[PDB]
Length: 212
Image (cartoon, rainbow, N blue to C red; front, side, top):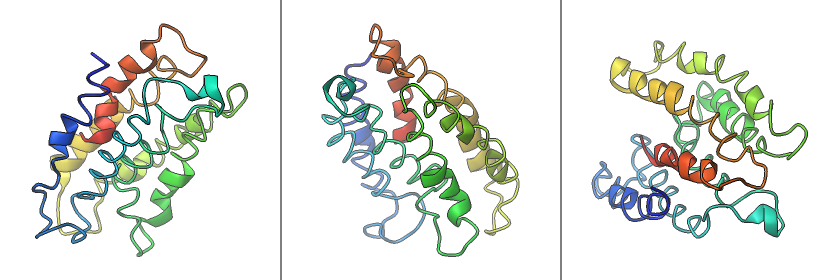
């Protein structure tokens, strides 16, 4: 579809989603609350607010041809930090204080999803490549922190069991088996072919970054 899944879904349908998580996700009334389910609107804010601000903002691909090497469409400094790893799991709602959570999982974020965007450039070299693909030389060990987990929430009073993890982690090991690959063929990037593989394919899965 895109346009009008890039820029209709998003803004005008995943906002409608985000009018909102919350018009009601708990809040009781309004969610600073909380730290679950999440964050409500801080991920669903930092997911509508960009995919608005970084929606136009975000249109198609531009910056490489203008000056700076990449950031609109791959924001991804407001699509994969934010939303996405302000909730992949967490990565920054939990970011707890209490040290098991933490920088194992900021280990996943500013470490190996930061290094997963600081990770799509250098546009040669390196850093294109096995820094993001070193992240997926870790998104297997670390995925088997969350696949050691969550056959291991030794840190609640709940089998979340199939009911949230077998959801998320299969969404991960499918829509992030299709969150590292078709951004070769969603611009590795080169400069930039149809352009349709590009972003029009890719952005079917931008959806997943917003929610689901």
